[PDB]
Image (cartoon, rainbow, N blue to C red; front, side):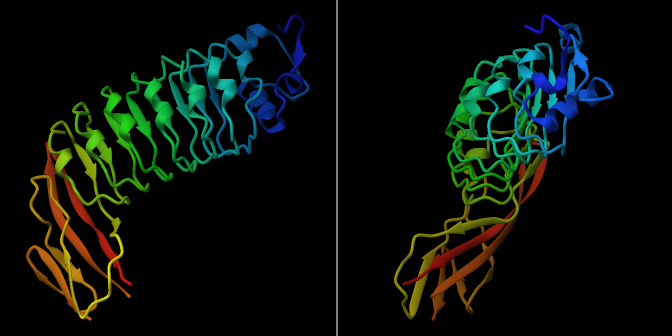
Length: 280
C-alpha cells in the first residue's frame, strides 16, 4: 500500500514503463512521488513502442480499462491478472504466450495478440465474452477452442498455420473474418456464417503428404469452395494438366495455383492459394 507519496521509479521496476507512467500522469520526472489517488484515477495507459520489458507495478493501477502495449518487449503478463476492469488490451509485437494470465479478466471485450509467436491459444477458452479478437501473424494450428467464442463479431487469424476451419462453423455473429495466408483448402464449414460483411481468404499455402516420383503422376484435387465443388486449378507447374477431378503430370516437387470468388452472407472473398506436392 502506497501509504506515503512514492517515486514512480520505485513502484514500476522497469525504467521504460516508469517513463510511460510519468508521461501518462503528465509528471516531470520518473523520480517524482505519486499518491495512490493519482494511480487510482488512470483509466487509460497509452504505451506503444516504448521498449517495455515488464509491466510489473501495473497492479497499483486498479481502475485501468484500456491498455495499449503494442510494439514492446513483453514476454509475460502476470501483472495484468488482477486488472479486473480491463476492457481493451492490445499486445501486438511482443513475445507473450502465457494467455492464462488473462483467465479471470471477465470484462475484457477486445484483445490483440498479433506478432507474438503464439502456437497454443487454448487459454482463450476462459474469455467467452470476447467481442473482438486479433491473432494474425502467429504460429497457430488448432483453433478448436474458438467454438466457445460465440459473441465475436471480429476475428483475425490471418498469417498463421491453420488448415481446419470447422471450429468457426457456429460463430454466426461474425461480421469480419480474416483468414488469408493459412493452410486452408476446404471452405465448406464456413457456409453458415451468413452475417459476414468482410472475409479474406487469399494466399493459402497447402502442402500434401509426400508420394513417389512417377512418370505418370496423378494428384487428386482436394480444394473445395463453400458449396463443396472443386476449385479448378488455374496454373499448374511443370506443364501439368487438369483432368477433373485430378491434376496430372508427365514428369522432385510439383504444384498448382487455384483461384475462385466466394460469397458468404454479404461478403465477397477471393479464395486463392497454392497446393504443393513434394515427391520422393
